[PDB]
Image (cartoon, rainbow, N blue to C red):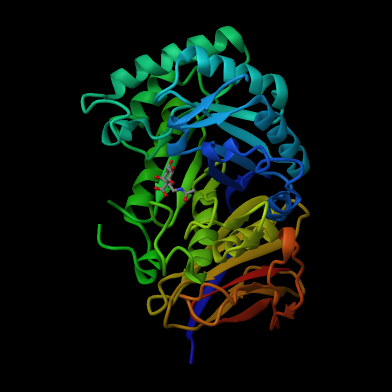
Length: 433
Ligand SMILES: *[C@@H]1[C@H](O)[C@@H](O)[C@H](OCCNC(C)=O)[C@@H](C(=O)O)[C@H]1O
């Protein structure tokens, strides 16, 4: 007995165009201690990335980038590791955001590392260097003293920028690689707008706010809306686009029973669209090893698997790129966590991404504004919102090496230019007209 809601696709309410390199993952720089990880020999992980997008961005940084030390002969990055990363990026078709050690390393070491990266990976595949991860939190791990402020950071950033550009005159940069805030990200954009390609921000649905639950994770985040508005103002005031270079559901590798659940797939897929509709250039979900929130879990020795969050990213992958249209929801007060995104695809077909994040309400969606004859739906499903497994998209799990294709396509009940789509509570759908 579903909530009956109306969705009006207005193909004339033009939103932002989703770039083809929108999707991405964030990893710890420490993973590069192991040259077998980001390697042309790591076909399994390479396969998982190709499935998330023919283009995308691998971001390497995180808290371990303050403890990772480049050497041409505490974790150590070797020329072998950088050489193997170039071969990895060749197998995936993805571009690279590469963190440099501004926390504990020297300008001269960062310049040397940046030179070897540009020499091996090249200007086409290297999107940006980043000078430190979350510099606003250096003072909390003692990487800097408590007195460290934006002024001190700007001094450090300039010293590193100068040293790297002497070795790498075409070196591209992004920063400041943390959450939107007025004490760091606004002044950074103002001072360094001529020295960076784009602004890099982070976002965790968990706050410092009450404890994170599946219930909480499905609701709007006023902090997210605030931070996104901040980044749009910085883009208006400076011309700098923004990318969400580190994101996931909960901090410290995630929360067992939230981050590792089917709920995370609905949250992650919806987030991708909410940020793309705000004009974000892209996203990088943080992950690695077996962390609770990792899209892809595993190791080269034991192999890799898609975790539930991966399936939300997979729905985005299958929607593909294009321009977002108006998709207005009515009669939805009793089903308020249903979200919907309409997309004019690059191939000229209309697509709708629906996230029924209501944990108790089934919906009946009356779709108008699509003058196409017919549509098919691929469902994003698990039997409970807190399932750690049993997740499918298009009636299939993702297999070894990111192997996926749909096994259940279901024609959409259509008649007189109106379509009716049923969705279970805590489910997602991709409609292709
Ligand atoms: C952003 C940080 O830059 C990340 O280092 C940090 O990840 C920590 C756990 N690592 C993994 C691979 O699971 C992340 C977080 O707190 O989860 C953010 O603080």
